[PDB]
């Protein structure tokens, strides 16, 4: 089936580096330069063979057509009130970017407030963050181009949707918080750097600072309120307390769910915001997370994991700050993870828990923490919510594997809290009643029971004849919960596939202990967990190795790439999206330095020892047995992915093609596709999203020779 020839890629055999005595050769190190003629030519040549391969079979067009049809359904976000107006995001169905609407009343005629679609013909300019002034009369929003993390902040006057001249540059991984006096807004920015800052560069991001922009002035006039010159990796985000009296600074270093918490009583500033604020270092260490919920005078309510892996709610009185004096408002649950908390209607708290990877939502009393109301939900996830302290109602969105979702509304001024369906959309074409979702718990190598959701058509015989799509992430305390995916459902309905999502360690499904079980020295647990998920699907008869496809993105790209090297015999197809492949050099580029809390850093001998054992780029090896070859592999990345620089995938594919691709027994393709005007994934336009899934499933279909089921 291989009618193409892999591109010629020069090997710099002199590129050898010493890692604590261990000599490591990196022949494709030159691919780290995205601007060179050599790297450009490499990308061109790779795409030259990948595209014709993906498009040869008529099934890509069949899939694309069905995806365009089924994905064409109205998509709404929860309504949210700002000042005297309501706002909500809405996509009629196939618009590249969702549009922000405004209405003066819940029953009023809605009108377009912000339409990103008119900013670019291909929809590559997207909204990335926003913040309304306390009175809801002014609006700040970030814009990112071509999928880059870089943001340009612009402003508008809400009444009449008037464009203002204020523009803030060099913004990245930024907060956006208006002071309640309506004078200005806090945000983060990086210092000027040589070269480009458009998402194609690989430059490390350090020395992020906290600034204050006074509306109606030039950015050059902005006030520097916080900086950490001696700690280049610290990032401090600001937020105003609900009463607007305190600026809360959450300082992070790395990706662990921990942060320092400093505060500033604005009343105590000698003469407003004129420089470095009089920060009071309440929590001055990275031992725990302190997520502000609300405050009543000096009593501040925080969601924390301090001495509580599953999270809980505590009250810290600024006037009696010692830890021994803190009050536990809502104790840690023995097993359920408290995902997030919101304060609404002055004294109500909305708590969202994760119970065996399914969300629950309930209302509690602020004063005592007592449970007041349970909002009933089917098995799924809460993916949207609205209701701030001054609001007297909440909106929340629920989604699941088989249904787009429902937005519920609950007027909290009523004695009887009666939540009601506010918006409910159904996709004509897919009958949810024909499929079923089951949750099982399989033992990993070490005996640990791992949860896994499996979605499939009702009544299938478990004879191992079905193609399967196994997804995983496993890291950064991220919980992989049920979500509605039209693309995955087409795989089930039109390709006769079985979907599976494994909640491997490293994630946050079972709190910080689950997270720690898949990081640093224990990172291998993630891989073992995932390989065991595949083994379960095979043993139980859901699929067979040759019909199994694994997929993951970013840290999940690392997941599937490592699994390909470790157990090539267990998979038929592997699709790794924007994955971290060079585990020895990831920390050198853009924001990669932040991931060391999950992976460790090669600069450390101990860490290098863990890393070198699983780093995808450094573990490509021909299977010893003549009857085993590498599975078909497709790496997807884009030229503006400044989160996980493209060099990771470029070097990995060059290695795969050389070491494995050259072997006579290797008949399965090893390809890469580098998209243009796209990045890590956030803000990607609908047009590109459709092209991407069509590529993915067309790849699976051709490699496994799967017939389309109309």
Image (cartoon, rainbow, N blue to C red):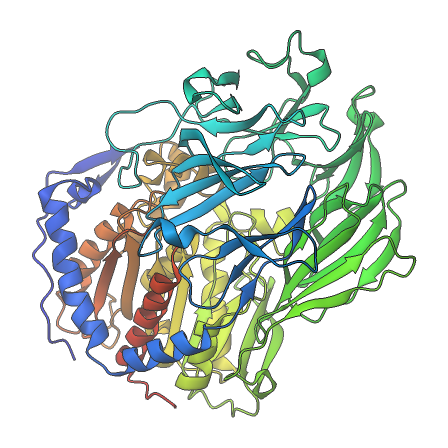
Given residues 301 and 233, the one toward you in this image is 301
Residue displayed at 60% across by 61% down: 448
Residue 575 in the image, given as x and y percentages of width and height: 34, 65
Image quadrant assignment for residue 378: bottom right
Q: Residue 559 appears at what percent x and percent y? A: 41, 57
Between residue 373 and residue 561, name the one nearer to us: 373
* Residue 508 in the image: above or below residue 246: below
Question: In the image, 60: left or right of 453?
Answer: left
| Outermost right residue | 415
Q: Is residue 213 visible?
A: yes
Relative to 274, 117 lies left or right: left
**Does residue 70 appear to the left or right of 299 in the view shown?**
left
- Name the quadrant of the C terminus: bottom left
Question: Which quadrant is home to the N terminus?
Answer: bottom left
Task: Determine whether 605 is above or below 660 in the image.
Answer: above
Number of labels in the image equals 0
Q: Judge left or right: residue 398 versus residue 58.
A: right
> Can residue 335 be seen here?
no
Give coordinates of residue 87: x percent, y percent. Answer: 61, 51
The residue lying toward the viewer, choosing from 168 and 554, is 168
Q: Is residue 167 above or below residue 526?
A: above
Q: Is residue 661 above or below residue 16?
A: below
- The x and y percentages for residue 279 are 64, 16
Q: Of all residues shown, which one is farthest toward the top?
A: 270
């Amino acid at each position: 089936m291989l009618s193409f020839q892999y591109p010629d890629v020069y090997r710099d055999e002199t590129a050898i580096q010493d890692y604590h005595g261990h000599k490591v050769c990196d022949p494709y190190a030159w691919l780290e330069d995205p601007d060179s003629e050599q790297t450009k030519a490499f990308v061109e040549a790779q795409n030259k063979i990948t595209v014709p391969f993906l498009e040869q079979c008529p099934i890509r067009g069949l899939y694309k057509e069905r995806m365009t049809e089924l994905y064409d359904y109205p998509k709404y976000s929860c309504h949210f009130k700002k000042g005297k107006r309501y706002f909500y995001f809405y996509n009629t169905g196939l618009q590249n970017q969702r549009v922000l609407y405004v209405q003066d009343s819940l029953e009023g005629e809605a009108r377009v407030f912000l339409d990103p679609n008119i900013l670019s013909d291909d929809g590559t300019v997207a909204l990335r963050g926003y913040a309304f002034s306390e009175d809801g009369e002014y609006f700040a929003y970030g814009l990112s181009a071509s999928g880059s993390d870089w943001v340009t902040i612009k402003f508008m006057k809400v009444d009449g949707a008037k464009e203002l001249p204020d523009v803030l540059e060099r913004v990245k991984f930024s907060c956006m918080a208006w002071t309640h006096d309506g004078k200005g807004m806090f945000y983060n920015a990086y210092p000027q750097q040589d070269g480009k800052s458009d998402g194609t560069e690989t430059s490390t991001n350090l020395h992020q600072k906290l600034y204050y922009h006074v509306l109606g002035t030039d950015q050059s006039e902005d006030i520097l309120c916080a900086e950490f010159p001696d700690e280049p990796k610290w990032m401090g985000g600001a937020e105003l307390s609900d009463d607007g009296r305190y600026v809360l600074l959450s300082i992070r270093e790395g990706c662990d769910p921990v942060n320092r918490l400093w505060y500033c009583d604005l009343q105590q500033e000698s003469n407003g915001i004129t420089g470095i604020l009089k920060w009071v270092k309440l929590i001055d260490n990275f031992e725990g997370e302190y997520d502000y919920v609300t405050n009543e005078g000096t009593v501040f309510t925080f969601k924390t994991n301090r001495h509580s892996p599953n999270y809980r709610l505590i009250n810290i009185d600024f006037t009696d700050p010692e830890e021994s004096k803190w009050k536990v408002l809502v104790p840690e649950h023995e097993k359920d993870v408290l995902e997030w908390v919101a304060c609404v209607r002055s004294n109500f708290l909305v708590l969202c828990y994760l119970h065996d990877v399914k969300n629950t939502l309930q209302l509690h009393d602020l004063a005592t923490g007592a449970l007041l109301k349970i909002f009933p939900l089917e098995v799924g996830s809460v993916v949207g919510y609205s209701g701030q302290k001054k609001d007297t109602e909440i909106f929340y969105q629920f989604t699941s594997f088989l249904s787009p979702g429902i937005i519920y509304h609950c007027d909290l001024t009523k004695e009887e809290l009666e939540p009601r369906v506010f918006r409910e959309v159904t996709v004509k074409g897919i009958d949810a009643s024909d499929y079923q979702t089951v949750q099982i718990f399989y033992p990993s190598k070490d005996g640990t029971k791992i949860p896994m959701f499996i979605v499939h058509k009702k009544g299938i015989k478990l004879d191992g004849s079905h193609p399967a799509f196994l997804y995983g992430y496993g890291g950064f305390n991220i919980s992989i919960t049920p979500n509605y995916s039209v693309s995955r459902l087409i795989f089930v309905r039109h390709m006769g596939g079985v979907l599976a999502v494994a909640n491997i360690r490293g994630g946050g499904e079972y709190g910080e202990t689950w997270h720690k079980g898949g990081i640093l020295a224990n990172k291998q647990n993630c891989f073992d967990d995932f390989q065991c998920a595949a083994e379960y699907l095979i043993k139980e008869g859901y699929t067979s190795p040759k019909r199994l496809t694994i997929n993951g993105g970013s840290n999940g790209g690392l997941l599937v790439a490592t699994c390909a090297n470790q157990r090539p015999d267990l998979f038929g197809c592997v699709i790794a999206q924007v994955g971290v492949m060079d585990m020895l050099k990831f920390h050198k580029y853009t924001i990669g330095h932040a991931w060391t809390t999950d992976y460790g850093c090669s600069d450390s001998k101990q860490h290098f020892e863990w890393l070198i054992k699983y780093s995808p780029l450094h573990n490509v090896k021909l299977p010893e047995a003549d009857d085993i070859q590498y599975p078909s592999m497709l790496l997807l990345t884009a030229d503006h992915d400044d989160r996980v620089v493209p060099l990771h995938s470029l070097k990995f594919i060059a290695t795969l093609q050389y070491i494995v691709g050259r072997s006579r027994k290797q008949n399965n393709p090893l390809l890469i596709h580098v998209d243009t005007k796209a990045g890590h994934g956030a803000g990607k336009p609908t047009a590109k999203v459709i092209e991407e899934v069509s590529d993915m499933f067309a790849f699976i279909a051709r490699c496994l020779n799967i017939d389309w089921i109309p």
